[PDB]
Image (cartoon, rainbow, N blue to C red; front, side, top):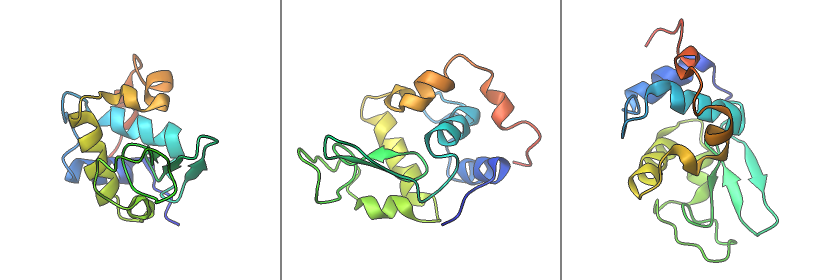
Amino acid sequence: GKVFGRCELAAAMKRHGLDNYRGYSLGNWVCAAKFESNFNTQATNRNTDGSTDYGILQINSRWWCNDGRTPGSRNLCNIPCSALLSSDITASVNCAKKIVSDGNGMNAWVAWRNRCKGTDVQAWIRGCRL
């Protein structure tokens, strides 16, 4: 039930190589997490289409992770969705890298597109020890 701080999450994401991953600076990734889950690793959103969004980046169970419940499941990250609810961000980062890598940009994340794109995303790392 870990809720990250801004700078703590930025450092963790940097350690996992997300800074400038496929051209997306670190602040984009922190901004996305802020507006997807407000940094709560346990965040779960259960949709009416039978899919669920899991964890700090709200990764969806139709294409990305397997929860055994979701119609049309592709499990392209090859993981159980429960791995995305850990206090350790490893599985979420690894699956986020796949999302980007499997054709998508960060437009895959509705909160990134609607609340981060075009903004001064360096503000989300400002003042942090990285």
